[PDB]
Structures are given as structure tokens and as C-alpha cells.
Image (spheres, rainbow, N blue to C red):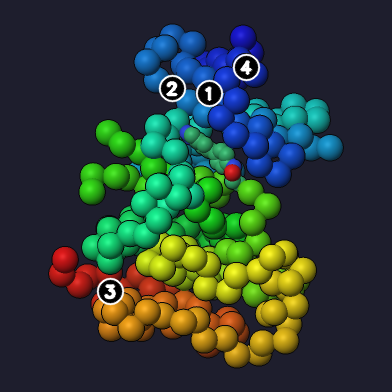
Amino acid sequence: TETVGKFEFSRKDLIGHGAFAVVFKGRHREKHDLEVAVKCINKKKILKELKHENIVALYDFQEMANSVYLVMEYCNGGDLADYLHAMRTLSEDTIRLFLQQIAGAMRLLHSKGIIHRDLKPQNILLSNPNSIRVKIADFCGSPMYMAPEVIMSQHYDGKADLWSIGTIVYQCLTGKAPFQASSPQDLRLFYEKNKTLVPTIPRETSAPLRQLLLALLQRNHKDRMDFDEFFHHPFLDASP
Ligand SMILES: *CCC(=O)Nc1ccc(-c2ccc3[nH]ncc3c2)cc1
């Protein structure tokens, strides 16, 4: 049993792996009821006070000489990747409920000038007490969700997250990524050669969802909708 401030965990209770990182299940040393995820980063913020129902809370952190430990809110429902694998696709009404929650979380991050950069289904966690609550984490390996300007090592901004959300919502609607690639290098070459991109949207898609997806899935960030346009898009206020 190891401890970080008022929290404890065993390396036997592995939740997942990230970039040179591992995540263990742990708990409050006093309140064994309060479960946490402990992220151990190998070296090889505002986040602590940043607080939203759709953001995984940071309860504590601890830099050591070669290691960094984050004590995070425990989410019991797995990730969007698992949900999408089970359901294959989601209804527009479920997509809209998911997107309202992501948009709220992203608005707070945009407010504080924070850009996620690696939004993907494995970083969008579900919490069951739809009533499904989504929580964004890490504010791996799959490059399908990275904005073109990111995978081509350019000067990107907040708009990179809008590309990622576009690719996630497209996969929610259709069951597939909009620009599928055997490999990163292929995806990087596809975006290099294709200065224009039109994703194929099923004709049955509602006009507001089609309009939103075309506005997010713009190859060039100058043409991509900005955060305020996304947050207030008519799709997010349309009736079920
Ligand atoms: C980069 C994506 C990935 O597959 N790794 C990963 C693993 C585990 C978490 C995580 C974070 C916070 C949390 N709270 N309860 C459960 C978890 C899991 C995130 C990303």
C-alpha cells in the first residue's frame, strides 16, 4: 500500500496505461468509501481548483524526483470507446446529451485558455450514479482523433479540440472514423495531400447535426468553427 497525501493505492489494482503513465485504483485512507484513480507519470496546476461536473476532478498531486502522482475522481462506467464498441452507434438524442456535457466542460477549459490536444473516446469517461454523465480526463496511441495541424506539427490552438470532438461525434453517429487509416504515417500523408476534406455524412442525418459536423471537420483551422459557434450551435438546443 502506497500513499499520496490522504490517499492510498496498490500497484496490484491497475486501471490503465497512458503515455509513460499508469493508473491505479485507490481510496481515501480515512473514508474507504471514496474511491480514486491514482495516475503515476514517469519523468524519464489550475486543474486542482478547476471544477466541473463534466471534468474528472484532481483531488491531489505530488512531484517526486523522477515521478508525478495525480489523485483523481474515480469514474465507474468505463470510457466512450467501450460504450461505442458495445452500442456500435448512438441515437442523435444520445449524441446531443453527450455533446451538451462535453461543450460545458470545454467552455470552462476555453475560459482558462486550456487546450486538451488529445481528446479521444478513451479519455472521455462515463459515470453511472440517459442519466450517463461524461467526464473528460487527461486535461492511447490512436491518431484518428488528432487535428490535421497537430499531426503535421504546425501552430495549432483551441480549434484542435473542435476537430477531435467532430471526429468523435462522427464515429458516435456512423460507427466509424471519418478519415480511416491503417497507420498514423498514412493518416499524416492523407492530410498532407488532401488540402480539402469532405467527410461523408449519411443523408438520414438531421440538418443541424450535418451542419455541425461539416463546420467542425474543416481541414484548415481558419475555416473551422470557433468555440462560441460550437457551444451555441442549434444542434445542441434542438428538441429530442
Ligand atoms: C490516453 C487514454 C487511455 O487509454 N488512458 C487512460 C487510462 C485511464 C484514465 C483514467 C483517468 C481517471 C479516472 N478516474 N476513474 C477512472 C479513471 C481512468 C484515463 C486515460
Point out the frontmost of discs 2 and 4.
4
Picture quarter with the C terminus: bottom left
Instruction: Give the CA separation, mark 3 to mark 4.
Output: 44 Å
Per the model, the C-alpha gap separating discs 1 and 4 is 9 Å
Question: In the rendered image, which residue does mark 4 sit on?
Answer: 12
Q: Are marks 1 and 2 in contact (CB under 8 Å)?
A: yes
* Position of residue 23 measured from the top left corner of the image (x, y, whole percent): 60, 31
Q: Are marks 1 and 4 in contact (CB under 8 Å)?
A: no
Query: Is 139 on the left or on the right of 232, as rendered?
Result: right
Specify the label residue 25 is tagged with: 1
Q: Nearer the viewer, residue 193 or 49?
A: 193
At which x and y percent is residue 62? 65, 28
Residue topped by disc 2: 35
The answer to whether the beta carbon of the residue marked 1 is less than 8 Å from any atom of ligand 1 is yes
Whether tag 2 and tag 4 are in contact, CB under 8 A, the answer is no
Give the label, 1 or 4, closer to the camera: 4
Q: Hey, what amino acid is under mark 2? A: Glu
Split into quadrants, the picture shows ligand 1 in the one at: top right
Q: Is residue 126 visible?
A: yes
Callout 2 secondary element? strand
Report whether 99 appears left or right of 148: left
Rendered image quadrant of residue 111: bottom left
